[PDB]
Amino acid sequence: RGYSFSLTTFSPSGKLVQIEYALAAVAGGAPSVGIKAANGVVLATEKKQKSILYDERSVHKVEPITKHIGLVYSGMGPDYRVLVHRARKLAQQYYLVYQEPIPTAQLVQRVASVMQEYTQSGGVRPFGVSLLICGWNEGRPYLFQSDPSGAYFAWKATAMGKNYVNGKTFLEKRYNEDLELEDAIHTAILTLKESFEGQMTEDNIEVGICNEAGFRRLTPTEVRDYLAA
Amino acid sequence: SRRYDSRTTIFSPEGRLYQVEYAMEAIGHAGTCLGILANDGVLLAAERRNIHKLLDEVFFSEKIYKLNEDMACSVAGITSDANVLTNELRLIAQRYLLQYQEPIPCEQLVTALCDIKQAYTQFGGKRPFGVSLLYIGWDKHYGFQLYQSDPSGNYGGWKATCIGNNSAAAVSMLKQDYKEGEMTLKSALALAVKVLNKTMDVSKLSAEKVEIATLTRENGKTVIRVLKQKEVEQLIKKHEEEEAKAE
Amino acid sequence: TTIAGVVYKDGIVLGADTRATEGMVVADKNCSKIHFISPNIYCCGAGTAADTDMTTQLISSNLELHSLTTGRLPRVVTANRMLKQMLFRYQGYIGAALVLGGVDVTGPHLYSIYPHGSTDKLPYVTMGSGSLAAMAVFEDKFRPDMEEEEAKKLVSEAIAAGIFNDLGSGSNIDLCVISKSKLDFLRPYSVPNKKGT
Amino acid sequence: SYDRAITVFSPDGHLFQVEYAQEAVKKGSTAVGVRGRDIVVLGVEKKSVAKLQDERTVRKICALDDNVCMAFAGLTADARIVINRARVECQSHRLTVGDPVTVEYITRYIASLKQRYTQSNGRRPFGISALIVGFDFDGTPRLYQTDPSGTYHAWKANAIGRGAKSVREFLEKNYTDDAIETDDLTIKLVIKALLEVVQSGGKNIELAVMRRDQPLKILSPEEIEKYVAEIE
Amino acid sequence: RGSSAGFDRHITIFSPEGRLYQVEYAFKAINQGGLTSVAVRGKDCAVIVTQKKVPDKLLDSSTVTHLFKITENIGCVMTGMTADSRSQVQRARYEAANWKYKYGYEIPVDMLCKRIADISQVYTQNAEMRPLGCCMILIGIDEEQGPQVYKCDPAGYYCGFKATAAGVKQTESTSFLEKKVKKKFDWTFEQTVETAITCLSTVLSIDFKPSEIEVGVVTVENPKFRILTEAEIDAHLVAL
Amino acid sequence: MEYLIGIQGPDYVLVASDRVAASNIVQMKDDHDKMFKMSEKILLLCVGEAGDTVQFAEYIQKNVQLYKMRNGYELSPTAAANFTRRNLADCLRSRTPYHVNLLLAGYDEHEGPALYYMDYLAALAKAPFAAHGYGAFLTLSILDRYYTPTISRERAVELLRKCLEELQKRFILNLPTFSVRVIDKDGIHNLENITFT
Amino acid sequence: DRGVNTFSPEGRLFQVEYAIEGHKLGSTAIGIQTSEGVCLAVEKRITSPLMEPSSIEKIVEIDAHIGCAMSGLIADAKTLIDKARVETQNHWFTYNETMTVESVTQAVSNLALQFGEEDADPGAMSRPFGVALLFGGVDEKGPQLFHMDPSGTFVQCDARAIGSASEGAQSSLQEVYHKSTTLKEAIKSSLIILKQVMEEKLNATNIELATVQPGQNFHMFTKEELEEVIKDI
Amino acid sequence: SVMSYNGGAVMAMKGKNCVAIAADRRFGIQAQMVTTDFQKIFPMGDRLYIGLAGLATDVQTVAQRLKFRLNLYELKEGRQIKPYTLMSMVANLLYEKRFGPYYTEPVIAGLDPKTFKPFICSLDLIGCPMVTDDFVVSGTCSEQMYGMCESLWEPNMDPEHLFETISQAMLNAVDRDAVSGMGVIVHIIEKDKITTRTLKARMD
């Protein structure tokens, strides 16, 4: 009926190697990038299909949670789907009780609590995925990041997946605090371009934005114009 | 199945508890935190561990967590477990207030939490929380207090303690500069700054590698106020001046 | 209370009055009875107002979830099924009566839902305490495949007849027009009563 | 639910978990208790006081009821659980039978709990040993002692912890109906019985006395200090 | 390459690389049966073809089928372990009936696929059970989009395709189909049966008789899932 | 009916009660105790249905004693009153509700005296004087007429005697004896009984 | 390695085989059945002269006509003693008569082997008990003496000895006993063998002795009568 | 009736950037007064009060559970609650006991924490929220204060005239109710001030 003992334990040096190994799994996903601007945030991913047979339209990596929140991932997709489903349920319960849209910080706290529960229960492994949350509430844009352990942060510009070290090393230089959302998109795209090993196309990447009006992922017809420059 | 069990809650051939011994060594490498008690209030002073430029300081603090109208704490170890513990402490305080219509005392709060920490070491098969806490507060009976818990589940009242990294040398130098009964809040701040300045391997403090909170009673009300960067900078300047003057 | 809906050529028109009472005394003079369920589905309510509020909020949350999970517009048949299954599960103890209506990929629909959980699809319907007064007007003047302006005129006249002949209704007329493209909300549509100067 | 046999038999009929629990209780700070004519006294050793604690919060001598008190050795976190359960039991007994408990009643309750944690699934044994003293309605003082296994006896005087191996030999030879005549005689007896195991010198000791009146009185540091001078 | 530490190769816990070896073994279990499937979708049709190799001639071959019906307009083909695939088909049928009962209309192919995929993700996480060693392919007509072709796997990954191929010869059977999506929309007309049979035969060299395959069909003209007769299969085979 | 009274002064909280334990037309007892001491400075008085009183009062007392034994100090009168209200209200809608009418008197080292009223619906008040029973109607207006905020204990016993005498003259029940005690700084002090032999 | 329930290449149940070895480390007891009653006797095995000897109770009373003497894990024996008391009181309550030594031994033996670690009960045992018992009493057929093991096998004896010196105690009991004893010669010989096998000196405070006979109830020997008997011997 | 067993009367009125709430003090049982200092108005926030009427035990219980939940909310989020959010939370609390409900009818009055825009609302026993723009009432003299407010109310009133109107309404309303009276307390929630007053009423 299920195991009752933990699978994550302490080591003679105080480490949790199951969590370290879930992080090593995350370090082998596809690159992700987030950049917070003066009036919005931007999420940009590498959606590179294995071969031409795969129908690109069917599966997406940038998903909404409410009318003002959306997130991307790096790591394992089947785990990402479970997390997305539970986040949607969490937001609906909050709205049911308070008749108000949930704030991004409360959303991130509840999601990280679930991810932490999966480090100390019986007979389970930790999730192999880190998240990048986006939001806008009370006239301010937010951008958080959640780890496989259950620890969340807050950034101005970050990068996940493969080549994240060089990603943030390059991201630090250009970043300005006065940056507009439309000029931030160029930097997000350029950062992805540094490590792509190929040729950019309207179906190689996904891009989502969030401003005053809500969350939405750009359409390939718009990604085309943005890639033209 | 028995093959995969790891037996987190058993004795060792010498009477030890290995999982707790290992969680203590986990807590050994965290960021330095220190507390000091005085005549007119208590103070906490932690160390900022994440100093990356691209971060955001949206929160009013990083390791403070006001638990009630009269108390507050600080953690060392694993943030993910710290969040669970802080939620539990808030719930305990509100249940007490609902039953008696008075605020809870600090020793009762610390006790009710250490019971939960202890029940994770005797049965269940789980692993224990890798977190140490410090508390500060004020109540009707004993006034300003300062406690400390550990993963095993035993606490104790103090007057000037320290957990985290290099806490051994921190307490060693605390023993020689603390004088019972005569310390005021300002001399407390001075000693705290001058202890943090040494027990951190960096050349000198930065007023953003630190984080300082106090607690006082004013007009029959408790005030818990996190100090500001300018105030901290002024304190550091004062420390720099007097130390330089002596030699 | 008086609620009434109609099916015209290219959509739905709903309506209600705006007076809440408590026994024999007017409590509120602007009580809103047309609720949001989805960007294309709306609902009216009569009976125990707390039950109406609770049920419509729960159904709206469930439909938002379902739409997020599929990726397409929701359906009046799905909303109707959810509602009737809940109301039958509670054996009539939740005293709400509903006039669900919308427009989906199949076209305009209009249902009636009762406290015990029985439903009925129709081209026009009324509910409340002036329901007989509105039904007389509907029987006398309804024509199939009507146009928008005349549908609005007919439903406003039915609501007014219910307002002027029922002691438990009055004070204003709301209208909500749903078509395949627009979603028009008219809260102070008509003001037949003015307080004495 | 966790249902595993943690403590099981071994070749030659040993219970290794209980033996390890006892090897753990053999590392605490020494405690000593004797039974007087009209008084009972206990005494615990403090390894180090650290010049910075608040001793009001690290006391190893509690009060389970008006006439019963105890003192332990082993693990403080386990001792606390046992003590609170004993308090709730005392209140239940008072409620149901309208009379304060006997010392043997509460000793039996504690020993039953300790034994139950040696035969249940998914538990480890407690790692503490207790010394229970008090008076009864007759006016007869008692002194008992429990074990991590659930066995308890009644003793004239005893010592638990480290160094008890020599405290017992000292107390055996020196215990006599002469050192028992008066309270300031028995208290000096206890003090010199504790001092040869305290190798720090001076007073690093806590000492509580309990008489038929003014229950659980605890000697002040200054008062305990006076007795040390008298002995020398 | 990837080191090991502890119980990595016995339960679903992370390796020092984060690899989950116990899930890489169900993929090898897929290649145990020794069959191969191929699904192709066209401008108005979806088609399934399946090898039919009976061991010797005492079996009633009217019962040895890899094609299944989930609802009236959804069909499926399994590959891998037989009893596993039977349990998965039962689960899919129950999911499809419950959807209709709850929401009043018929479940879409992608929704059914996602349900099966999250049911399998749970076997990838808890340690007391094992992953099912079978693959799945689905087809159907969507009233809004048209023809659809989806595929799950034992890891919980459920992408959508233009033309799939699962089984023992997966790599080369997809390398063949790679060359033919260049132009003419891979012969987007009711005769993609030609393409499917040709792709199945090219890397197997069998030139099958009129009864060593099974084919299934959905169309926009008739939406229900039909299994073509031997004569119909023979005519296509004869033309080849 | 049983009788209860309490009078709070500058630093005392003088209370009283009766001693009869009737069952039917007969009288079973003549010196019954309707006061439950729970702490060195807290008294609890009870009336109502048999079984309920003692079952309810002993539970409160054991919990107060356990609190003291755990924490090293005693509950305050306010905390005890609120704990009592909670425990009484949580039983109101349960399967077995009590039917007790209470009166909590106390004295604390900061706020001074305190007198709490509590009916069987678990509504808690605070008053300078109160009373339970049928005799409350007859003795509430003598206290109204003669009470003073700065009254001394010598006069307070005078006023209580006047109330009991009025009861003796005008009640239809036979209540001959009454207990009387005071809670000042020095704990509880039993006083002389008042008999009307 | 193994579970608690695990046969061996000889079908032996390892855990029971160990709980049985846990008895050769206890203090010897002795029972003897006569035509005039039964007698039980057990060594107390004092450790140091500071321990009160009136605090070692190894011979308890189950009812007004049954007594018990144990050896092994005195902490474990107490649940068995309690359950035997409760069963006897239930039998009295229901049938208005006294139970029988056979029925009590049989009901107590049914708790043994009732252990396990999966689908057992809400709170169940995790190992076998480590106590051997000796029941004595009188009923509608006369004095009887039974014996119980951790495996759950109970027999009926007339002179049994359990403990760490039994392989030497029975070698004398088989020569001493005969079907024509009286309880007095029984008591004498039961004392002589104890003295024979013990390590200390058999005096009047490091032993225990009780008797049941058809006339009286369960009665324990006093430090007056016991001393007189010892001196008389 | 059960909600007429302890009496009570609550009232809230809206002005120009100011709210006002009022209640009576009498606490009694069916036909007999016990005390005259019963509290029926609770400070849920800096400028956010709630007034409860009905059964006094349920008044106390609901106030205490609400304070529980609001403390937890303001500790978890990090800011103060809004008047609209508080109303929804109270409605949820009351609807959780739809069968076997509390006998209490609440009233909310506050100021918007950033726009300083007033807010009044009342809920029924089961949790039905109705928001108005002039005034709300609740208690045993509801009809009397309806008759008073409809006649005396004006739009865009100052705090002075608001106080005069709410006091003059409560006085004459409770002067015609048997189980209400013993004095009236009035809170005036302005932007930077909260003024409290006690009126002189009749004691019969």
Image (cartoon, rainbow, N blue to C red):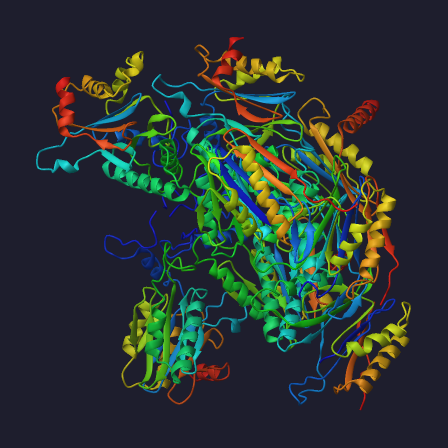
Q: Is residue D46 above or below residue A218?
A: below
Task: Tell me which corner region of the image, top left, top right, bottom left or bottom right, holds residue E186.
Answer: top left
Residue D181 seen in the current view: no
**Horizontal side, residue F66 vs residue F103: left or right:** left
Number of numbered discs on residues: 0
> Residue farthest to the front?
C140
Q: Is residue H47 above or below residue A198?
A: below
Q: Nearer the viewer, residue E152 or E9?
A: E152
* Quarter of the image that includes the N terminus of chain F: bottom right
Residue drawn at (75%, 27%) of the image: B229
Residue G153 seen in the current view: yes
Q: Nearer the viewer, residue A135 or B51?
A: A135
**Horizontal side, residue B101 vs residue A172: left or right:** right
Residue B48 picture location, percent across and down: 66, 29
Residue drawn at (63%, 53%) of the image: C168
* Quarter of the image that includes the C terminus of chain F: bottom right
Q: Nearer the viewer, residue D221 or E38?
A: E38
Task: Tell me which corner region of the image, top left, top right, bottom left or bottom right, holds residue G31.
Answer: bottom left
Residue B179 picture location, percent across and down: 79, 41
Residue B123 picture location, percent across and down: 49, 51
Residue G45 picture location, percent across and down: 46, 68
Q: Is residue F4 above or below residue G141?
A: above
> Residue farthest to the top?
A229
